[PDB]
Amino acid sequence: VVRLPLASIRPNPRQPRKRFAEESLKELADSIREKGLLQPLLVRPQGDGYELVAGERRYRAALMAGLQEVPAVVKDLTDREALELALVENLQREDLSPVEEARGYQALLEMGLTQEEVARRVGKARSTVANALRLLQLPPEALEALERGEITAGHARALLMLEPEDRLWGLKEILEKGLSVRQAEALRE
Amino acid sequence: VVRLPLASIRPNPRQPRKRFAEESLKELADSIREKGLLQPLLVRPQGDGYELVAGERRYRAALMAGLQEVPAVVKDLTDREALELALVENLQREDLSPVEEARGYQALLEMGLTQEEVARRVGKARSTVANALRLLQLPPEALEALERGEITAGHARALLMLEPEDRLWGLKEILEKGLSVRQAEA
Ligand SMILES: [Co+2]
Ligand SMILES: [Co+2]
Ligand SMILES: [Co+2]
Ligand SMILES: [Co+2]
Ligand SMILES: [Mg+2]
Image (tube, rainbow over all chains, first blue to last red; front, side, top):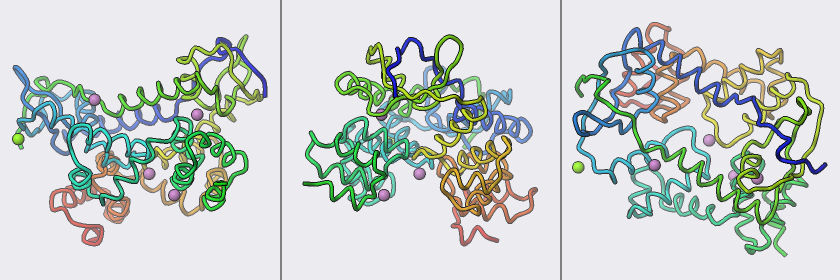
């Protein structure tokens, strides 16, 4: 381990995640050039025309495909509803990390919803929503380790049982020693 | 449900996912200002300096934090090993849909690894890797429905049992008629 100047470290040119998104976007586009759009886009009225409300990839693939017209569903939605829909469709993706899940629920709450309505809108128990929100009181590095898959939701819950000022220390212990959730619970002392 | 000129539909300005990524980057940067990096960056020699091999967010947050130096581990990695590492670190994330997982595996196979070798590196059974790869023979629209959470992996497997020419039709039935995995298999 050494100390290097940031100015002498260039970004990682390998971005497989981005490459995969572009590949699949193109593959979706190629397919619709033939049969047109799969399922309806969701839009709302805006000025002279419309504004996309749901189906961004579907929408962008249609553009790549060079289509002139696409099937859609027009619905009068206020800015607030459009945002709520954006958050909800996002929370349904197989893409969701538990941290993003929590940020989504929190955003819905800030918009005036209750855990109940949130839970309903997403199809989960109120307790599931409350438990996800708790993750947001963890320090940023603990949430990053969770997203990287270096620790589990269980490790995170154990860290929440430690006093705030001991959480980083606890995180290090878990990472350095490959602790299980059970042993992370033993860290309290 | 009606048809309308694509050119009359403008982009969705609401990008909560991107907004969240930016917000969390900043809070991570704010935290690095106070605590420094929790884990060294992994880098390899490149040109007159070094090139990041793992820890992109930690790296960018450090830049945002205004740090001049950061802890790091230097290793001599060939382009191939660096890519392999990139694909493996991505496959460990709590961020993947089963389709991305499949694409990652396939990428590793294309690099010369064996299903067995892929399985060993990501900590999964060989059967898990083979099953995931099967998802890639599904048509693009079925994979999108999976990624959007409109259908489950179970539905996807059910569609694999149908002949290629019937998969799109099958997808529509599942979405349109709203049947379950059980009902799907038929
Ligand atoms: Co970190
Ligand atoms: Co867990
Ligand atoms: Co937004
Ligand atoms: Co997941
Ligand atoms: Mg209304």
